[PDB]
Structures are given as C-alpha cells and as structure tokens.
Image (spheres, rainbow over the protein chains, first blue to last red):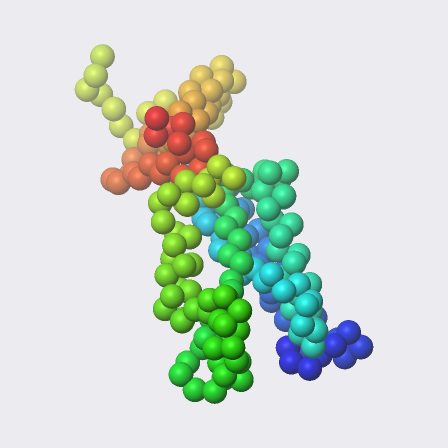
Length: 145
Length: 64
C-alpha cells in the first residue's frame, strides 16, 4: 500500500488487511481444528508472525500498521484460549533488510542510517535471523511462553 | 495369556456395553495423556509405523 492515507482507505486496503490479519487467524484456525480432529495434542506448529515496530510512524501505508499491530493479540490469546497445545507464537520484529543490488528506492539511504550506529541487514542475514527462530532452543521457549 | 490377538478384538463388546465403554476410554485417555498414543487406534486400525511427538508442555511430560 503506497500513498494511501486515512481518507484514501478503500477496497485495496480492506482486502490486504483480510490477507495480513483475518485469513492468517483463520489459517491458525484451520490447523487447530485438523490437529484436534486426529487427537494430536503434542505437536504444535510454530507461527512466525512478521511484526513491524513502526506502527503508523510513517503514514501512507493504509491498513498495514493496523494488520501488523492486531497480530500482537495472539501473544495474549495463546494463554487465554484452548489452542496452546496445537500452535505456538513467535513474533519476529523485522528490522531494515536491503533488497537486491539495484536502487530499490530505500537502499541509497541505508548507508546514512548506519552512521547513526544502526545496522541494516542483507536478505541472507535476515533469513539466518528468522531461521534462528526455528533452532531447537527457541523451539522450547515458544512451547513455554 | 499372550498369543491370540486379532484386529478389533472385543470391539463388538465396546459398541454395546456401557461398562466396556468405561474401561477402554479411561485407559485410552491415560495412553494419550502419558505415552501419547490411542490404544484404540492400535486395536481398530493396526498401523505399521506410529510416530510419538514431544512438542509442547504436554509433549515434554510424555517425553520425561
């Protein structure tokens, strides 16, 4: 969603939100039922939630922020509902990742941002970090908290 | 004693008798909650490979 502020929120925005929140919940919904059916109580699937820290700091992103913030409900519903044995939540707050090696509009300023003592990531580096969330140690953590 | 065991032995009795239903289920509930399989599934279907998984707080207790 580009150049879509509050007033310009329409079809596109709602549809994206349906993708970026509702169906993901329904997907977590679907897997729970199919696991509860076969009496599989002891093999939870780990859901890697793409989190943003910039919950509407930018604007023009339409219903991006709303989707990405609403996911944080799962960190409380896991305690309070009956699906803790079938799913676990692993919220990934993703930082800066430089895309390919051309001028994808944001790569030019990456250097400038790193001169504030920030570090930006390559695709392969961020991947490693996310694959870090599937290591048997943090697997155990998801299955406690 | 041992020896004489077929697929779905005494399952005819499980369907009818209330007392039978008590015995199997209460055992079956324990097999799931402690050793993580359905003894019924074993008797009824007689599978070839069964995989026990130790994921989640409940899985941990079964692994221990």
